[PDB]
Image (tube, rainbow, N blue to C red; front, side, top):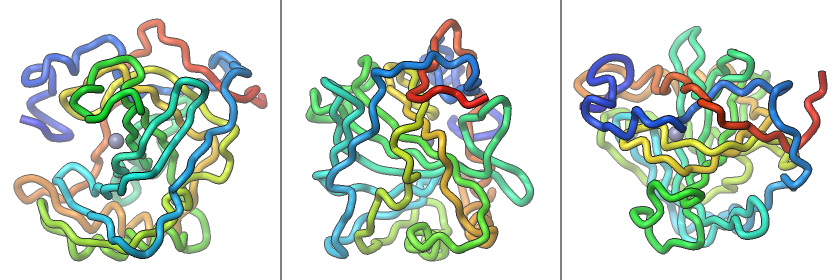
Length: 255
Ligand SMILES: [Zn+2]
């Protein structure tokens, strides 16, 4: 009815998942259109105080952190957004699980911060409308040191190991979960990557990654359980054909 790696393949139950402009996609940087209109991203309100706490929950498909009101993200003139939630996609032991790929390369994991256009008061109004939702996406890679910002979330996974369980976590700097380079990114129009696969979503994928320790990546991929009694692993959708869409780059590809 809705699960990674099997049946139903999604269009049988959610026809919009067979649309022509779906996400995620494979990014080929030498083929992206360099677009100097794409200026550095602007975030405000992402540095949260310790109280009030946020909600962290295992929904069977990911771990999702609900963000409080007041987080603003600007992609450019006329493209202002309010953050709603973030969640992650990952693989398993020795197997990467990012959703986007770069030249076919899959990264260990990926963070998605989902936002609602300021044109709309409610998510339901914005579904399927061009630009109504925007997602910021960054790849997570292995580095040598523990990532202190991620540890605030990863240390709480054990208590929400069971599908459907929830907890509360202190406010933290949400921007410290994202790359520091706000100037280099790719952007394209796609869809939600889970059913109902609604189109019109503006995807922004940072070029720079974030680094977590090997232990932290194991904690992320190995702690949670999903539907039935499977481990919550490999929770990524396969990449989708561009079907003529152009991916834009905010920076000149190096090579
Ligand atoms: Zn996602």
